Image (cartoon, rainbow over all chains, first blue to last red; front, side, top):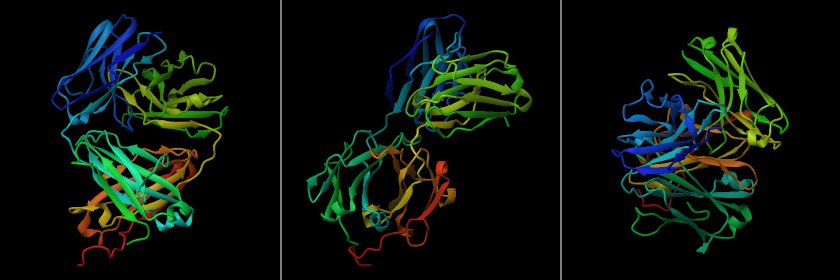
Length: 215
Length: 224
C-alpha cells in the first residue's frame, strides 16, 4: 500500500508569504495520480490540484503542484488569510486509495489583545443544582493564552474546561471560552468569582470578576 | 444542480447497522466511479470504498472489508453504503464523492457508534451587562449544556444575525455529555430595544429550544 507522509505537520506564515508543502509516497506513483485537497472547518475537502500538476476549476493560480515518482509538492505562492485550512495529498494509483495526514496552515497577523468578559450562572441553571461561570476571551492573536479561575482569591483547579474557535477566515483571530463548573452548594459558599487572563497583547494579567448575587 | 446529497447516518449501537444514501443530480451519474470516504472527529480523511460505473466492480479499505457493502442504483442516480457490525472505530463523518478533473462532494453525514443514550441539551442565557461591555459593544450568548450525541446547531434571531457570532466547539464533559456556548457581540447602545434569541437545534433528540437572552438589570453602575 502506498503511504503518504506529509510534512511539515503544521505551518504558520503571514499573508504574502509562500507555503511549501511536501508529500512523500512510500513507492513510485507511476502515472501522475496525485491530488491535493484543501479542507476548511465544517466543510468537505475541496479539490485543488489533480494528476500532480493540473489546477482544478476556479482554483486561484497561487496554488500549484509539482513532483513525481516519489516526492510531490504543493506551493501556495502568496498566502491570504482565507487560506487557513488543512491540506491533504491523495494517491489514486493503487488501492487502498490513501491520503497524507495533512498540513495544518495557520495564518500569522499582528498581536491582538483579547477582550475579556465574565458571565455569572443564570438563575435558571441554579434552580437545577449546578453553576456554570463563563469567561470569554474574544478575537485575539496569537493563540497562546492562560486563564486562571480564582474563587475568594483561591486558585481553582480541575473544575474548568476551555474551548477555542478555529482561526477566523478574515481577521485571523481566535476566541476562547473557559467554563468553570461548580455545584450550587459550592457556588453559594463563596462571594468573588474571578477570571485572570495572561496574553502577549496585554500589558500584564487582566482580572475580570463579579460578586455572587449582585446586580 | 450538480450535487451529491447524503443522508442516513445517526447514532447506532455497537454491532448494529446503517445504510447511507447519496443522491446525485446535475451530471451523468452512470459515467463515473463513485466513492465513500470518512473522517473521524478531529482526524484525517480515509477512503472507505469505490464502485465502478455499473456496479460491476467494488473495492474496500481492509478495516471495512466484509462489513460494508457499496452499491448504486444508476436509474435512480443513487449511491449507498451498507454498514454492518459497526464498531466505535467506525464513528466518523462519511462523505460520498465523485473524483474527476472536477470533484463533487456530498455534505457529509455523522455516524456515531455508541450504546449511550440520546439526551437533549439544556439551554441557559449568558446575559449581557456592564461586565460584558467595552466601549460601544456588548457580548451575550447561550450556554448549551449536557447533550448527546453531536451535533447541536445554534443560530441567532432565526438566522438573521450572523455577524460577530462565535459558536465554540463542543467539549466532552467527564460526565460523557457535551457542552458548548455560542456568543455574539452587538452594539451596547441598543440592548434595550433589540431582541436576541439563540435558536438551539439538537436533531438526534428532535430538541429545538429558542432562548431569549435579556440584558441584566444593574444598579451598581454610574447613575444615568
